[PDB]
Amino acid sequence: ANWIHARSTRKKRCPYTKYQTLELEKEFLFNMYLTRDRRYEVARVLNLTERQVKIWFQNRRMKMKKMN
């Protein structure tokens, strides 16, 4: 977890929390896009930054753009 068993860090299956993915999936339904309104409120409940959440979705797309 730190050095005794820490080794693979390029995997990350689903070490996320239910709350985090909750807000992420809630918007994907209707709020397909991210606006200052959502980014702000969702950042207050997810304890993230207005840009942190936006950049999160953006990056996820870029990797799919340039592909592997």
Image: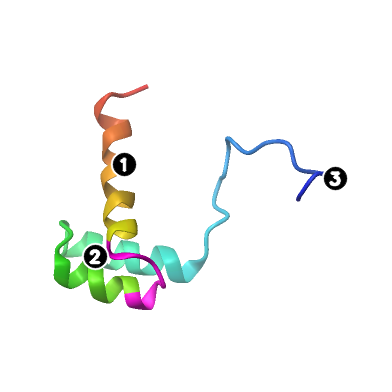
Q: Residue at x 15, y 67 (%)?
A: 36
Label disc, if present, on residue 9 of the rendered structure: none
Give coordinates of residue 68: x percent, y percent: 37, 21
Give coordinates of residue 44: x percent, y percent: 34, 77
In front: mark 1 or mark 2?
A: 1
Does 49 appear in magenta? yes
Q: Label 2 belongs to which residue?
A: 27
Label disc, if present, on residue 59 of the rendered structure: 1
Q: Residue at x 80, y 44 (%)?
A: 3
Q: Residue at x 76, y 49 (%)?
A: 2
Identify residue type, mark 3: Ile
* CA neighbours of label 2 inside 10 A, class few (<14), some (14 to 19), many (20+): some
Which residues fall within the magenta stretch? Answer: 44-50
Q: Residue furthest right?
A: 4
3D distance between C-alphas at marks 3 and 2: 39 Å
> Secondary structure beneath disc 2?
helix
